[PDB]
Image (spheres, rainbow, N blue to C red):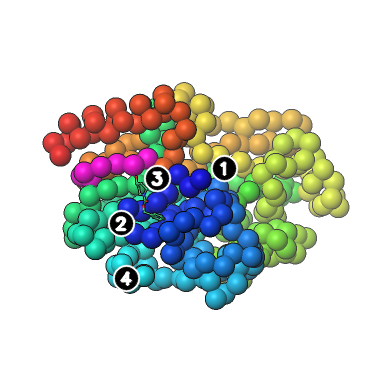
Amino acid sequence: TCPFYKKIPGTGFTVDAFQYGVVEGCTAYFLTHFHSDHYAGLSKHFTFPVYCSEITGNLLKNKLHVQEQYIHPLPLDTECIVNGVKVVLLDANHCPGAVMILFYLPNGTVILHTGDFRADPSMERSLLADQKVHMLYLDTTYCSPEYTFPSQQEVIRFAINTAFEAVTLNPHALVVCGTYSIGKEKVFLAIADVLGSKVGMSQEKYKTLQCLNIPEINSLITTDMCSSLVHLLPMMQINFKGLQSHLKKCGGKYNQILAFRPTGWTHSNKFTRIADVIPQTKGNISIYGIPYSEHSSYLEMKRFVQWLKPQKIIPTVNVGTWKSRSTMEKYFREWKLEAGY
Ligand SMILES: O=C(OCc1ccccc1)N1CCC(O)CC1
Ligand code: NI
């Protein structure tokens, strides 16, 4: 059973709704981004039209093996007609290829679906500036005031400076970065650049990165682990046991590991500043958890919504409990009363 919040009223469209079989009445399936909770159910045997960005389309074809005849990539920032309805894709400031979708309904209603996003003041000068939005389907992942974290720029400055210091003190240190999906590529790219190295990884992860349209990517990444002093590993391996095991495989080239776990928010955000962050250490291994978010903080989300002034908000995250739903509804009303819409 497809939930109501994945259906767009007055259309035959669904959004991120691939795990419910054939949805009755659906003439086009939109996919906002290539994260597994959103693409769940897509496979090589899918036979309906999928609308998405070019980058998402590359990943569908190459990683999931969806046949090319069912993949409909659309350019960003461009008015397009899909089954008789005007739509626009906008950058969501999430992972590579992630979009928000503007739907212009035949009856004059305008709907914005944010997919997953990290709201930014730059969105206030997109094609959103032009007209009124009646309904907002909102990524509410962090819709509570306890969810604070730094800018992406601040977190990258910390990572670059930490890695450059450690490897300059000990040239035989290896840097490892955890990953389990697309997104957060700036973490490993920025560290490798300050160290004058390519990033080494598995054939499978290399394939994924080759789909992302990153400028000059062949200069930045490699499958030749021996040539690289920044390695990527699955997130599940970023622990003392898994890193000890990896160090053994490196043939006595290295005598220390510095590792990074990009998380989203963790409760240590409610005490500590980024500047004060310390690692967990066992012997010659140290692990840093860094709060690199690709979702809106509470303050970023509030600013975006109070600027956009929607008539109705439909949450798409944390929808499963009465407590969560009640909390979100209280915040939306505060925001509306404060700003006067
Ligand atoms: O039928 C609905 O949308 C139209 C639609 C039907 C089937 C496939 C795609 C789209 N909605 C919208 C939301 C309403 O609350 C109740 C369900
Ligand atoms: Ni996501």
Q: Earlier in the sequence, mark 2 or mark 4?
A: 2
Whole-percent x, y for residue 46 in the image: 59, 64
Residue drawn at 24 percent across, 63 percent down: 106
Residue placed under numbered mark 2 in the picture:
10
| Residue of label 3 | 5
Alpha carbon distance from label 2 to label 3 = 13 Å
Residue 298 rendering spot, x and y as whole percentages: 36, 35
Q: Which residues are magenta?
A: 309-315
Q: Amino acid at mark 2?
A: Gly
Amino acid marked by disc 1:
Pro
Looking at mark 3, is its residue's CB closer than 8 Å to ligand 1? yes
- Residue shown at 45%/44% (left/top)? 3
| Label 1 near ligand 2 (CB < 8 Å) | no
Give the distance between the C-alpha atoms of the residues marked 1 and 4, in whole angstroms. Answer: 42 Å
Quick one: 148 or 194, which is closer to the camera?
Answer: 148
Q: Nearer the viewer, residue 5 or 142?
A: 5
Q: Label 1: which residue? A: 262
Residue 153 marker:
none
Q: Amino acid at mark 3?
A: Tyr
Q: Earlier in the sequence, mark 1 or mark 4?
A: 4
Question: Which tag, 3 or 4, sits closer to the chain's start?
Answer: 3
Give the crowd class for mark 3: few <14, some 14-19, many >=20 residues within 10 Å.
some
Q: Residues within 10 Å of mark 1 (few under 14, many from 20)?
A: many
Left or right of 14 on screen, residue 70? right
- The residue where tag 4 is placed is 84
Q: Secondary structure at mark 2?
A: loop
Beta carbon at label 2 within 8 Å of ligand 1: yes
Residue 228: percent from left, percent from top: 71, 59
Element carrying mark 4: loop
Residue 243, x across and y down, in percent? 76, 41
Tell me the residue at 36%/70% (across/down).
83
